[PDB]
Amino acid sequence: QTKNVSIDTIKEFMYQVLLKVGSDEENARMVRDTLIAADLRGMDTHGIQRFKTVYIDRIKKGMINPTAKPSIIRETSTTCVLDGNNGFGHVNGTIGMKMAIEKAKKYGMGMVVVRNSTHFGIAGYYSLLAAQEGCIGICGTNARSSVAATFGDEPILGTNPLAIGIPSDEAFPYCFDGATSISPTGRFEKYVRMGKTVDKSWASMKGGKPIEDPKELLENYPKGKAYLHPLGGSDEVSGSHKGYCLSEFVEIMSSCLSIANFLNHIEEEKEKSGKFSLGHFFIAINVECFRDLNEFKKNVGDINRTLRNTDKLPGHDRIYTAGEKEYETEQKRRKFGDDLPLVTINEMKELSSFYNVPLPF
Amino acid sequence: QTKNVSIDTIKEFMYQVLLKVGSDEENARMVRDTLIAADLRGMDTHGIQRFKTVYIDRIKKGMINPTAKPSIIRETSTTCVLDGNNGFGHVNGTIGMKMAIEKAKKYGMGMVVVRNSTHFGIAGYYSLLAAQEGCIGICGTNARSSVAATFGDEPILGTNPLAIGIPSDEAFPYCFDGATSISPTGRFEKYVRMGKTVDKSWASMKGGKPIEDPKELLENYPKGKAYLHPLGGSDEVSGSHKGYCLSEFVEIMSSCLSIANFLNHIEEEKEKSGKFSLGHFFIAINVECFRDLNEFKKNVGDINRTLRNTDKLPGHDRIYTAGEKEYETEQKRRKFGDDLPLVTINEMKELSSFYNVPLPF
Ligand SMILES: NC(=O)c1ccc[n+]([C@@H]2O[C@H](COP(=O)([O-])OP(=O)(O)OC[C@H]3O[C@@H](n4cnc5c(N)ncnc54)[C@H](O)[C@@H]3O)[C@@H](O)[C@H]2O)c1
Ligand SMILES: NC(=O)c1ccc[n+]([C@@H]2O[C@H](COP(=O)([O-])OP(=O)(O)OC[C@H]3O[C@@H](n4cnc5c(N)ncnc54)[C@H](O)[C@@H]3O)[C@@H](O)[C@H]2O)c1
């Protein structure tokens, strides 16, 4: 069962509750923008449906500093290292990428890395910021161990998403946004909620036995007794080594340049300090340094249009490109609202009650 | 059957034959270095075993200009566009990346893109150049249509490799280097030669029927009647959409910034002009702008060491990291030589005969 709430309601509510729990006002705006962006785009695991447990409960457990802003550790013409000061990933991310964009506009390219940060929601959000300014945007984050290396029998790597935003001449930019593992953990939380079984390729119990029940992974992976597979699965034959290497790429970019916790150290240091401390990276490339922007947008569109025009495999109506599915969901939800599960509705009611933030139900 | 030839013999021979067919001397050096690099690293599809048909025969058919050098079209502080002037990809690539490195050293980051170029051998080579200079190196190329989009029944995308080179405190750098499709076409040429069947996930006949016989793909994909799958296979469930999006990423980076042929236009324009005209991109990120180099090398090593130390799945002795397999092959071949198929030996003899380039057999 599900209840329809408008985007505006969800937007405003998130921002009021973040103020009530003592966020800096601009911080509340940055965080709710990237949270609602997840709901607008159909990443239902990364906005309101996770507002209470992943953000509010964590501010309550002192795991996030809601008034914190990043600090410049080392800055050059085209680069920067930021200490996240245990703030919102969305705060560090928004500032970091805006900063990378600013540097790209002045010099051609920009890269900003972050240490000592927290969960930053959808990777795609920061890449979208870059595409709106006529830059190619590449970004990612590490996360707590959930994914096994190739030939591994133990969670060691985060789901380590990579997002790539590229200006387009269409109504939406190209935007790849996804984990370097086949599945993220949030899809498992989702599949438990609606009581579906998961695909066999996504995860395995210790010893390599495939998982069909989403609960098995979620409970055992923090125990080091279950794990997710990289893109490419578990055999080199299907391409396992590639997703695994790409996962590591993300990890190194996220931790090695900023000196952030990596791999098993994320969870281990949370057991000591109470806080998940993570890294992020943000790259911006100024298109107009290479070619006219509209001429470039046209070329990207031409690639997309060509791709969608190729022969479709029987059984399938259409071919998509990166970010197409998200645009159509965004158009749908913008006008008709978002169908939220009952648990989320009840979480919202509870927050409304606690912080005296009015709700229309 | 196979005949052992030393790396030095292969190295020198390649360079003499390239001089004999009228290459600029420095060009012969750049090309043979990146060709032998393929043989040193165990990419047996991209060095001497392909010397005759992919390079020499093509210079003979006017498809490569062997004295050509790239031309600067548009240059900024951190960026550049090059016209490859129909030269060797290895020439354009080496110059392009060296140029991106040079800019990274001065400003923090560098990006050079190339249009109107040719086959550039192993992507990993250019990334290795960056890692040797203490930069993160990211690079790629587009190629003729061989790969189907997700839900597609037709080859449209190249195998579009992506290589990432990262400085390490180990004896070899981290180096991911591979196609964005599960398999490249060269692995198919290889499997025909030694008469093995290919995995079921790699390719399909028109209509989606898996291919077991490597010959079926090789003959039908240029006809538009067979195709390779992206990393992730053909179903979204296994992650198809990801490899597919990554493939497109490579394509856009390779063609849209430099104005190179893209997708179906590569083959189509070769049918008109006689020449495969391609794009490439090369990114270099100066580590020391962020963190001490050795401290960074140490962190990368720590990631690798942690990864290799995790529990190994029963049936498997060890876990590898990007570029490990290549280093061990390189160490082996450096001292004991390279076991070349009889066809390659015979190709070499023929070139020796034609161009009066001495061989020890
Ligand atoms: N913050 C974190 O630590 C973290 C960790 C993991 C994932 N995430 C987020 O979770 C979200 C979902 O990630 P996911 O791994 O489940 O991705 P996914 O499998 O849902 O794939 C999403 C991407 O693939 C594209 N796509 C989907 N189908 C396609 C098709 N048929 N053709 C072409 N493109 C197609 C979409 O446009 C989008 O770019 C992402 O927004 C990601 O940033 C965050
Ligand atoms: N020039 C072109 O147009 C073109 C096109 C396609 C491919 N290529 C080249 O072909 C070569 C082979 O490509 P491929 O797609 O067959 O790659 P592949 O499947 O052989 O994988 C190679 C990469 O994966 C790593 N690897 C392998 N096993 C691993 C493991 N168990 N754990 C961790 N890492 C592991 C290697 O270190 C290497 O980085 C590459 O050098 C590529 O550049 C070139």
Image (tube, coloured by chain):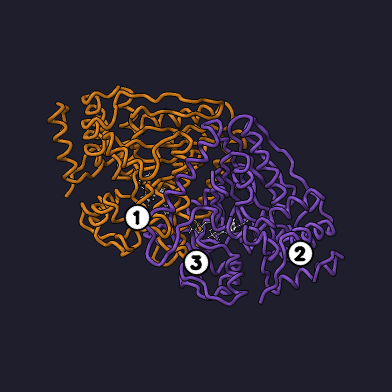
Chain colours: A orange, B purple
A225 is higher (above) or lower (below) than A167: below
Query: Is residue A295 in view?
Result: no
In 3D space, how far apart are the residues under numbered discs 1 and 2 (Cα atoms)? 50 Å
Q: Is residue B178 left or right of residue B30?
A: left
Q: Which residue: 29% across, 38% down?
A: A270
Q: Chain of mark 1?
A: A
Tag nearer the camera, 1 or 3: 1
Q: Are marks 2 and 3 on the same chain?
A: yes
B17 is higher (above) or lower (below) than A337: below
* Depth check, front residue: A170 or A343: A343
Which residue of the protein is positioned furthest toward the right in this rendering? Answer: B356
Q: Which mark is residue B202?
A: 3
Q: Chain of mark 2?
A: B
Secondary element at tag 1: loop
Query: Is residue B4 in view?
Result: yes
Q: Identify the amino acid type marked 3.
A: Trp
**Ligand 2 within 8 A of label 2's CB?**
no
Which corner quadrant holds the C terminus of chain A? top left
Q: Identify the amino acid type marked 2.
A: Asp
Residue that carries the numbered disc 1 in the rendered image = A154
Q: Which mark is residue A180?
A: none
A269 is higher (above) or lower (below) than B165: above
Q: Are marks 1 and 2 on the same chain?
A: no
Q: Identify the amino acid type marked 1.
A: Glu
Sequence-wise first label, 2 or 3: 2
* Depth check, front residue: B199 or B76: B199
Q: Which residue: 31% across, 65% down?
A: A209
Secondary element at tag 3: loop
